Structures are given as C-alpha cells and as structure tokens.
Image 1 (cartoon, helix red, strand yellow):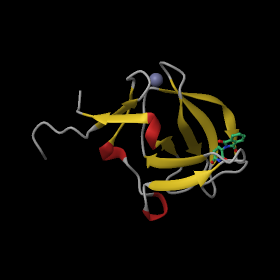
Image 2 (cartoon, rainbow, N blue to C red):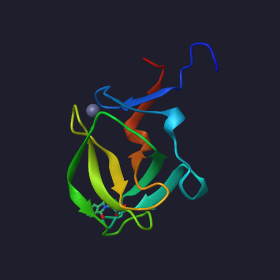
Image 3 (tube, protein in one colour):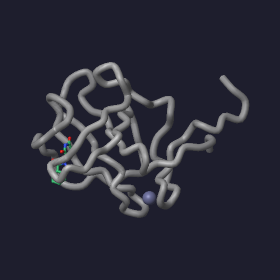
Image 4 (tube, rainbow, N blue to C red):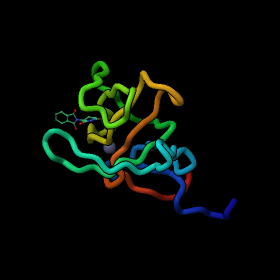
Length: 112
Ligand SMILES: O=C1CC[C@H](N2C(=O)c3ccccc3C2=O)C(=O)N1
Ligand SMILES: [Zn+2]
C-alpha cells in the first residue's frame, strides 16, 4: 500500500476509457511482457493481464499465428473509441483466458 499511487490504472491512450490495472498484470511463461510480431511484420510489446474491461471483442476466436501456445485469439478494441488495444486469448490452460494488450497504446495513471 502507498498513499495516492500514480501507477494504478491503465486507460486507452486515445480516449481515456478504463481498460486494466497494474495489479492485474499476469506473468505468462514467467514474464508479463512478450515481444512479438504479426504476419505483417509489426512488432508489439504485449503486456499480459488476467482481466480487462472497456474493450469490445470482435468476431470469433482463431488459433492462427497465436503467440501463446494453446490459446485462440479475438481482436480487442477499445469499446469507446475503437483503437486496437490488443487481443483476448481463450481456449487454453492455466489460465483458460487472458488479455494481451499493446503497452504503448495504453496510458498509466492514478486510481478512480
Ligand atoms: O497471437 C496473435 C494475435 C493476432 C495476430 N495477428 C495480427 O496482428 C495480424 C495482422 C494481420 C493479419 C493476421 C494477423 C494475426 O494472426 C498474431 O500474429 N498472433
Ligand atoms: Zn479508446
């Protein structure tokens, strides 16, 4: 516990929608940070979270190109502005589900 913490909540960088919390970071494979690339060669610094809110999960899951063995992904947009914030992963084991969010698309700041 700290008084007046400034690194508590992650919001959408583009609009401020509440998305996640530092307390919910999830060390997948021993690290909450996973640096990965997609088939279009884009590099993402992905932070894994157990939980997130304020997103909209688009479509149905796919296992194609999944960065996390045993998980299928759905695109996760900011539910307010539509910014692509990351992916929701499901269908796996321990945990069954989690979120992989793009670190530089979030803003971190004080609690609400
Ligand atoms: O775990 C994942 C999530 C999605 C992701 N990915 C993308 O970022 C992407 C962009 C364009 C076409 C196809 C893909 C897809 O598989 C990817 O490569 N792995
Ligand atoms: Zn947003």
